[PDB]
Image (tube, rainbow over all chains, first blue to last red; front, side, top):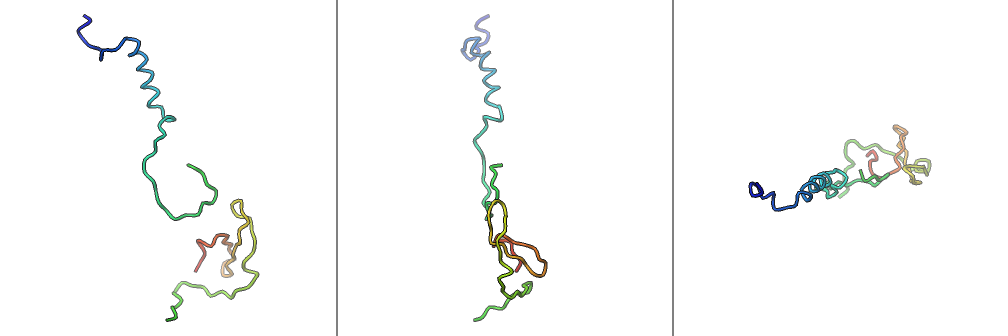
Length: 50
Length: 49
């Protein structure tokens, strides 16, 4: 029965942990590489990052 | 060559009463007020012709 699937050749615990890690990776707060910029000629009155 | 003043422009005699200090976005900007409307324009950008 052990040969029916390789289970990517990992320990069962590495799978169970891998799950929660996939939950970390797709947390919005981590996703901090930003894509694309808008060039525009404007005054910086009252700057806010957002 | 003397360029023509375009169509939308409003003549304004310069006077000291026009330019003044004013608070504007946490700065003491040299505001200009436009006599046709009386509106204040702290930034040189965005002022009426």
